Amino acid sequence: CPLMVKVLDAVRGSPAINVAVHVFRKAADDTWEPFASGKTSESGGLHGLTTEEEFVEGIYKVEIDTKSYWKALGISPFHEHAEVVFTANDSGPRRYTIAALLSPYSYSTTAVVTN
Amino acid sequence: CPLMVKVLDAVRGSPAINVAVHVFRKAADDTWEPFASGKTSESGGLHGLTTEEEFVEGIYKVEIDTKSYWKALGISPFHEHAEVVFTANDSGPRRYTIAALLSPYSYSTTAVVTNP
Amino acid sequence: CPLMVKVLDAVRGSPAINVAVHVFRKAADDTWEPFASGKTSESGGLHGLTTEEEFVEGIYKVEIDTKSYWKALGISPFHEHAEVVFTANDSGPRRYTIAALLSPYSYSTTAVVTNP
Amino acid sequence: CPLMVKVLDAVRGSPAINVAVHVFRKAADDTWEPFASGKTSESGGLHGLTTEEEFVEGIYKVEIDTKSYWKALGISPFHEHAEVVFTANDSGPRRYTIAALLSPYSYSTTAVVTN
Image: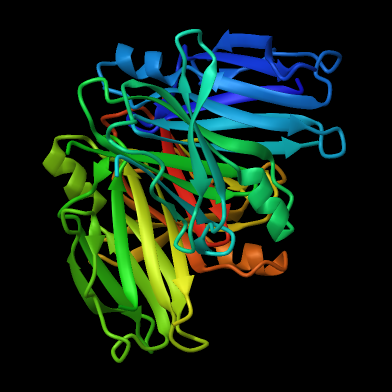
């Protein structure tokens, strides 16, 4: 698992469950091509997005559909989605976790890149 | 001043100065049209992006050039940029401040929205 | 103004108004002596805590009353308060702004430090 | 494991390893009594702090010794330590994770409370 995503809810202090996540890779013409997607699990995680084979160096965008998450809970959100855009570089450690902490009018995101 | 951006640096404990910021508005054809841009001042603030007249209803993307910022300071960053995407003004004009706190492998952003 | 505090609310997208803040200074006997306190204004800011004269070298604890804030707004919070502990002025006077962003089960804080 | 602590480094995008963590419980006289402590592991985690038996309702303070962490890495920090102070309440879910994300002049902390 070269790429994993973890999403938490700062209002309830819980995983953010069943949140849609779409990953895209930047194509030669600068457009964003779909690459992987899924919904977070009961633990706020999303595994099995890719394989080492498909996960080549490039620029990637992770879009987390936070607006749908909050609206379904009856809480008015500010963002359309949260976005994380980064270059994957084979020079550093192998595994990337993209963690996001959601509030209705804020979010934070960190990357943990380990071997 | 209906859209402002404030950017802080969590490594140095300072405003993030001379950070490029681009704002785009989603067009009828789902492409991202340029809308406004500028650079943060010595206080980490960016005013003057737009006017109540120009800042119509719409989906806007504020993209903060975090990677150039960290590279200028000599520090290896993870993200290409930090993006904040939101629907604006759909119940009338509001004033938006978008604040972001930057670290090399993390950032946060928040919005403060007031009704004029 | 050598110590200021700014507090934002990440649920409402607004400044956090009327938030109580207490500052303590560590005493020679390792107890926390009261130093200054006040409440955030309509802009989420708190000025006037102290003066360059009174703000001597020392270890300070800034405690922001997040629990009362969330309880007033009708929202169940996790923390008792948010605490920021730091050595101040040990190479001469500096100006400190302590910014905090509040959610019911999370908060962040950052310092901006400038040399006068 | 009723209480776990997870610490990440926002400068390197990695777990914050070998960081000292001390937990205290507020005593009847308002003083802080030691309760548990340890150092984070290679994964930035710290398990086995307490048992359900000792972890009763009360007010707890988690102090994470961030100044020692940064100074050893040659990076000048602002805080003495990061502190998380909260009441444990048996009314909600059982397990508490206290997560902290460290930068030299900032930190964020969240709690994930699950069953």
